[PDB]
Image: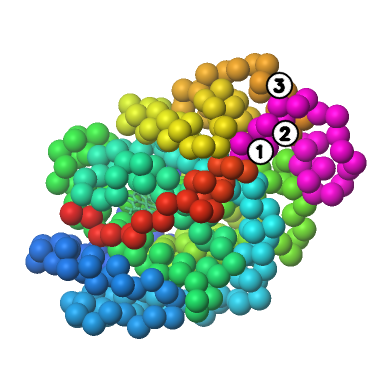
Amino acid sequence: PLWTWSPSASVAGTGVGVDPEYVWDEEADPVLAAVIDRGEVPAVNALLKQWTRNDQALPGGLPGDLREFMEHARRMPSWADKAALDRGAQFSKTKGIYVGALYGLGSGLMSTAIPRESRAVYYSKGGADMKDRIAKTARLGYDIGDLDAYLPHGSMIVTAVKTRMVHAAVRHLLPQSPAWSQTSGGQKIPISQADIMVTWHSLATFVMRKMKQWGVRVNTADAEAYLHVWQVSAHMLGVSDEYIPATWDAANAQSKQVLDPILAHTPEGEALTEVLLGIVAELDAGLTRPLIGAFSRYTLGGEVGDMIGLAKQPVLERLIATAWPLLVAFREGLIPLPAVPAVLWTLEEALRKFVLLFLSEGRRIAIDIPD
Ligand code: HEM
């Protein structure tokens, strides 16, 4: 379901296509199911913990099927462009407060309105703790934008391959949780490529849309660079090129059809929201529940905020909406200091500390195959 078009708008650009709802990860899935079934997860995790850098040889002692899978998965696509990648990274850094806010509060809360992500995350067993699991898209979205992401001394190739490996492992594990099977609707196997592309629109497409709507200065070169970083990242995550949009016009159209209609409240999503709100409110950021609620509602809009169960705070939301664009125009250098209500500056400081504490200098545990 979800997806109804051909891939002529895609990175691969071809006329034909298989429905991404019924494609998973043909190279990773059986390699990980074997690694899990031979009881090699503890050992593979101790070995992979040593592999932290894009240019590093794989550690010896890996099982042969896994080594082969990994040396192939760490390859950059031939269409990756170094100059665009460096530019997309610079852009992400220069707009760091906006992109960090939008990933951590916008995309991270929107995830709790995406039923399959919420159920998979909620029921997933043996992986990261709940505290880390809930942050996982935002912190990966964040690290995607790093200056070094795809350079030899960076780590995003590492992060993407291990992430791809984790998704493969979950395809073999989640179906054995009766709780996930019973609530899955008709889906036999979790995390379709279609599902991955839903999350992608909740990240890349959403963030670009909101930055342009708020008046962040996004010239055409930067916008395409940011897209490219995201296209290379979808590929490195294991999304086939036939599903990755080629241009912003394609990404925007695909998001209206693939993301918008699947947003929905679930009990599992409700539970995830409370965890995320509690962790964010517990950071030493000054980001209280009222401020998170109002800003997340302004960002996501009222229909998504209602599904999520963020309560409408009409005064605070109106103050934000009337004045946040002035603050943005001021930080972008376009207007003199604006007379805005003082609480906007409070909000802005709370957001900056949030990016700092939750993402920038945040917790980065090693990405482990689940048990
Ligand atoms: C561009 C899309 C996505 C990104 C960037 C992403 C990122 C990540 C990362 C970084 C992890 C590792 C955290 C960890 O387990 O240590 C992970 C694990 C996982 N992801 Fe995703 N993911 C995406 C899509 C999906 C989708 C669509 C689903 C489900 C429908 C999903 C479900 C999970 C699950 C269940 C785990 C294991 C959670 C655990 O640790 O217990 N992800 N993801």
Q: Nearer the viewer, residue 262 or 269?
A: 269
Which residue in the protein does label 2 denote? 345
- x and y, in percent, of residue 20 in the image: 39, 55
Foreground of the two, 295 or 183: 295
Depicted 91 relative to depicted 134: above or below: below
Tag 2, which secondary structure? helix
Q: How is the image coloured?
A: rainbow
Left or right of residue 147, residue 370 in this image = left
Residues tagged 2 and 1 counted as in contact (Cβ below 8 A) = yes
C-alpha gap between disc 3 and disc 1: 19 Å
Against 311, residue 28 (above or below) is below
Q: Bounds of the magenta span? A: 325-351
List x then y, in percent, for residue 137. 45, 49
The yes-or-no answer for disc 1 within 8 Å of ligand 1 is: no
Residue at the spot of label 1: 349
- Magenta span contains residue 335: yes
Q: Which residue is mark 3?
A: 318
Give the residue type at disc 2.
Answer: Trp
